[PDB]
Image 1 (cartoon, rainbow, N blue to C red):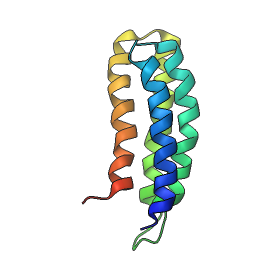
Image 2 (tube, rainbow, N blue to C red):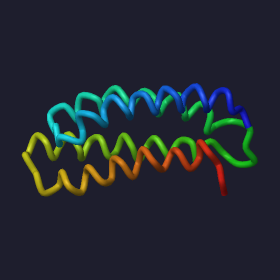
Image 3 (cartoon, rainbow, N blue to C red):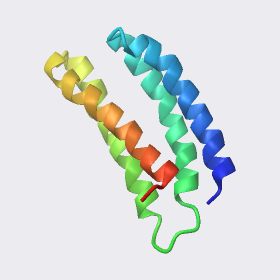
Image 4 (cartoon, rainbow, N blue to C red):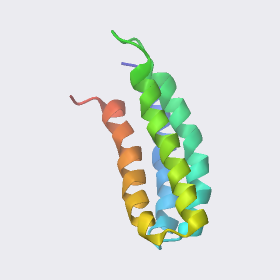
Length: 109
């Protein structure tokens, strides 16, 4: 397992997560969409590592980011409509989505 590659991306992820966490804690919803678009790029880097030497297709690495982008559409959509109700459901799913990648980054299974 290429730990240097995942470590580089993980350090970049932790620092990104740390800078946004400070603002996110305030429920700075308007600012939340700004950082969400920047972090989206970082998933593409981890994807390159997820599609490393495996015994099956690239589908696993592919579906992981696909769900994240599909979430971004409903996320921005709830802002446009002002669906505050949906923001609760969106916030938890965003943190649940970014953490899902960690499982595959650490691989403790």
